[PDB]
Image (tube, rainbow over all chains, first blue to last red):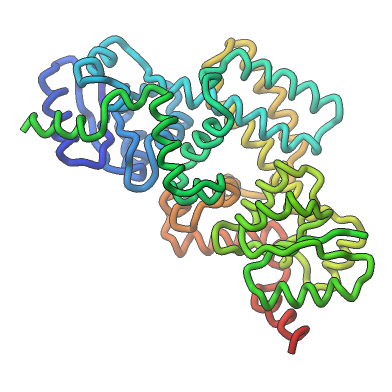
Length: 210
Length: 211
């Protein structure tokens, strides 16, 4: 079967999802967490095939969590709840073996981060050695660019989201008003296919499974 | 002249340093900032040669700030106040053209981060193209390794610090008690050569330039 781990800060949503996945004998809910810390301690212990995830968490966010989980467990499949228009489409994706768009997105971003890091640290190594690595690095990140559709500002914002910085920390770092950041985050999540249904619509759906 | 920018959240320390560098006609204080954000807005506008910096700030920290400043301004020389046993040794280092240890520490970290990033994002490209890239990255990072003296945990902490995370966010992410983080940070800073004198001793030194 498919071992599924649930990550969501709402009991009501966790219980509804447990109900949903329970009716499918092919699925096996092997644990749940209501925050980034819990999931970081519990997911590598349960070793699921798939993590089912809300982007909104009390102590960070789901982009941060996915990046952090993926570096420790590279083959983990990550499905954002609001990336699907319904729980049925989500369940189909699970059965289909879908990895989740956020996975490709995180890796795209890490390839691009690597270009920046070497870029910033290049005054340490040989002149010709630096240009050689720099060339091969951009080539790899230019081949694999799932984030090509984003502006620079959105790439940066995504980067900072993936660190688990708060909206206020992001605002301070990007010289934006906090309200503008909240808007930009939602614009960015929408652009990445992660606002296909609202948070309140997930809640109303899981709550009716009670 | 050497253009110097001061970053410290205590007015008493900024004034004392302004007094001190003003006595030297070879130095030119070109600006001051009392936070990460202020420094981020103001250093790229003043384009100093040197930033004189205290590791503790109200909205982040100096490792974070050096990292962010250096990515936009690669040639900036960054000198942490507590990396020197006295203001005289620090002034000597400004005169000598010293870049400051934090600079190469940060570039070392970045190289090592690049290894982890490609490590993590490698399932996207060719199996063979991935390895070749991976070898060339490690070879470049272990050849240039100023952080070699640190433990893995200290490397991770240093990375998290450079993102400007609070001690609480670091505790959460590293599964440590907050007071343990405070001790590990102070330990890591001391190991990096950045606690050659205390904060209180810097404060008392600048205070006696005013009174």
